[PDB]
Image: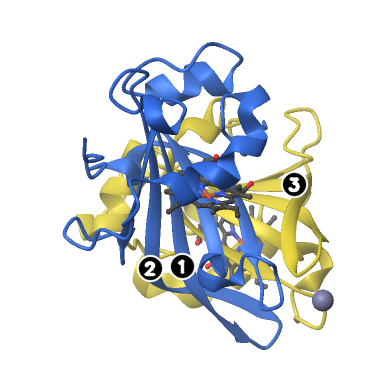
Chain colours: A blue, B yellow
Amino acid sequence: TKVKYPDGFRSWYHVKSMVIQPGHPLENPFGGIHHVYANAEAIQGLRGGNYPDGAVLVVDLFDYQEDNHALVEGKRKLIGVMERDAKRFSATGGWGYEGFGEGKPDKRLVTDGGQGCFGCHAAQKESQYVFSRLRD
Amino acid sequence: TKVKYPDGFRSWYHVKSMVIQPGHPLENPFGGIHHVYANAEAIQGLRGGNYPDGAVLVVDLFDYQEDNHALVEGKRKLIGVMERDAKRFSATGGWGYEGFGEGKPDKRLVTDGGQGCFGCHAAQKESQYVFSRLRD
Ligand code: HEC
Ligand code: HEC
Ligand SMILES: [Zn+2]
C-alpha cells in the first residue's frame, strides 16, 4: 500500500511545465518551477485511453532564483507522484499519491494515505484525476 | 549543408528549463519559457563524453501568460536546433544552427549559415559551444 519511488522518471516523456510564484493559492508548498513527466503507460491515458495499472505521473518541483529578469532552476524541492492501481489504491480513486522531499526515496511527505492529494485531484474526475493535458 | 528538422524531439530527454522575462537583454526574441532536449548522442556529449556526429540539441520556446501568480505555457514561439557534424558544419564550430518558427518544419529562420547563432555560442567554446549543463 506504499507508492514506489519512480526510479529513472527524469528519462520519461516531459508533458508540460508551469511556474508557481509567491501569492499563488498553492505557494505552500507547490511554489517553484515544476515539470510533469509521464511513463509509457501514463501516456496512453494522456492520449485519451484508460490509464492502465502501472501508469505513473511525476511532478518535479524546483526552487528558482530571479536574476536580471531570468528565472533560473535552483535545487529540487520535492517530487509528487501518482501511481495507477485501480484495486490497491481504490480508496483514492485508483491512484496512489506520494511526495518525496528533495526527490529522495526515504523522504516520504504523505501522512494521511493520500486523502489530501486525492481531495484536490477529485475535481479532475472527468479526466481520470489528472490536471495536466498532452500538448505538442 | 542544412540542419534536419528534429522529428520526434518532444520524446527526447528534458535537460533543463529557464524563463526569460521582460527587461532581459535577450527578451527579443528569446523571451518566454524554454525547455532544452537532447537526443542519445547529445546526452553522450553533455556527459562529459565529446559529441558524436548526429548529436542534436533542441531549445523549445513558449510564450507564457500570467494567471494569478502562475506563469502558464502559451503558444510555441519557435525551436532552435543544433546538429553535430564536425566536417559539414566546420565553419560554425562543428554544429549546424537552424531555427523553426512555431516549431514548424516549413518555417526555417536562419539566413546567414548560422554565423549569428554561432557568434553568441562561441563564448562556450570550452563546453563545445553548448550552454546547457546536465542536472539531476
Ligand atoms: C490542489 C489543492 C492540489 C493538491 C492538494 C495537490 N495537488 Fe498535485 N497538482 C495540482 C495541480 C493544479 C496540478 C497541475 C499542475 C500543472 O502543471 O498543470 C497538480 C499536478 C500534479 C501531478 C502531475 C499530474 C497531474 O495531475 O497533472 C502529480 C503527480 C501531483 N500533482 C501529485 C500530487 C500529490 C502526490 C499530492 C499530495 C501530496 C498533490 N499532488 C496535491 C493541485 C494539487
Ligand atoms: C546569445 C546572444 C544567443 C544567440 C544569438 C543564440 N542563442 Fe541559443 N542559446 C543562448 C543561451 C544563453 C542558451 C542557454 C539557455 C539556457 O537555458 O541555459 C541557448 C541555448 C540554445 C540551445 C540549447 C543548447 C545549449 O547550447 O544550451 C540551442 C539548440 C540553441 N540555443 C540554438 C540557437 C540557434 C539555432 C540560434 C540562432 C538562430 C541561437 N541559439 C542564437 C543564447 C543565444
Ligand atoms: Zn495577487
Q: Secondary structure at mark 2?
A: strand
- Percent x, y of residue B79: 68, 46
Query: Relative to the observer, which residue lies in front, A98 or A119?
Result: A119
For image coordinates 31% across by 65% down, the residue present is A101
* Badge nearest the viewer, 3 or 2: 2
Marks 3 and 2 sit apart, C-alpha to C-alpha, by 28 Å
Tell me if residue A118 comes above or below residue A67 in the rendering.
Answer: above
Q: Is residue A39 visible?
A: no
Instruction: Residue under label 3, please give it.
Output: B78
Q: Nearer the viewer, residue B100 or A99?
A: A99
Outermost residue on the top side: it is: A49
Amino acid beneath label 3:
Leu
Q: Residue furthest bottom?
A: A68
Alpha carbon distance from label 1 to label 2: 4 Å
Could you say whether the residue bearing mark 1 is in a helix, strand or loop? strand
Quadrant position of ligand 2 = bottom right
Q: CA distance from mark 1 to mark 3?
A: 25 Å
Residue plotted at (80% across, 66% down): B68
Q: Disc 1 residue type?
A: Phe
Q: Amino acid type of disc 2?
A: Arg
